[PDB]
Amino acid sequence: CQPIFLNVLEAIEPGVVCAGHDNNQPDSFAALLSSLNELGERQLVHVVKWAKALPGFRNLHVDDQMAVIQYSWMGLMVFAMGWRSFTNVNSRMLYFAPDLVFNEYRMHKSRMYSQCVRMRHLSQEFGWLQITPQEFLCMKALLLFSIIPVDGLKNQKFFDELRMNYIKELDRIIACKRKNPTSCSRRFYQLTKLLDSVQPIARELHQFTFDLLIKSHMVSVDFPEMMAEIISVQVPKILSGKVKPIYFHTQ
Amino acid sequence: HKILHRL
Ligand SMILES: C[C@]12CCC(=O)C[C@@H]1CC[C@@H]1[C@@H]2CC[C@]2(C)[C@@H](O)CC[C@@H]12
Image 1 (cartoon, protein in one colour):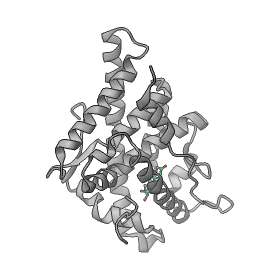
Image 2 (cartoon, protein in one colour):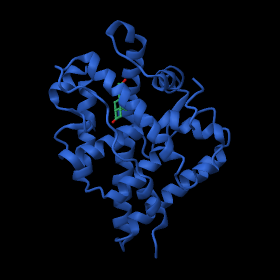
Image 3 (cartoon, chains in turn green, cyan):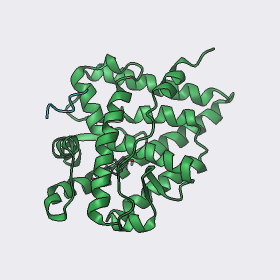
Image 4 (cartoon, chains in turn green, blue):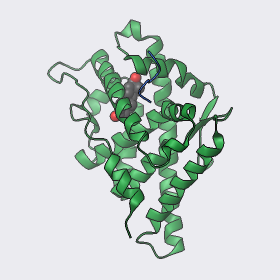
């Protein structure tokens, strides 16, 4: 049998994205954060093209297509960055981009050291849990459907159905080489715990970038058009409790 | 402006 679903996920996976950072200059808070912001703007373009090509994405109402992207981009990008770090440098550093790799010194200079250490822990988990390339792809897609508004989406029903379908595909990938219910159950527990762990990290970064935007003119940090719009209009909805992640486990 | 536009 042909793995149609997985064939598609592999086929649409975005290529390499560079930040455009000048690594010839001594590190500074302003330059490092401005480059992270530009990388965010560039990655946002690839995330939109990727999402629009996902199986069933068009089943969603137009307004909800935009909403899920605007709310889950931070988690999606952090998860992908953690995987790149694992595969390219065995979690020795944070591989934001080929031209923007963070060692401990840069983590400190960025003023978000604690958050950076938590992301490195996430990267290490990909190795400790022996996450396969196929599990990574399915889990990343699921992250796009893991944060919603308390007030509900325009067509909450279509969303619930799509999310359920991606969960079913994850079950299938888990059952592939496993011919025992207990083994599958144990793996599902591990993967759902890993997925939940992304949310608290994304929340801390949401708070950090929000505060940075508010005082950006005082610290010389540049925010591109799309990033500035999303962080001033959508991010505060999550910080004020109007939009919340869907956790598998209670915590 | 025009939101993300390329949605
Ligand atoms: C999503 C990005 C950029 C894409 C990526 O690889 C993950 C990384 C996580 C930290 C984000 C950064 C984009 C710009 C932000 C939001 C800064 O303003 C502060 C936190 C940064």
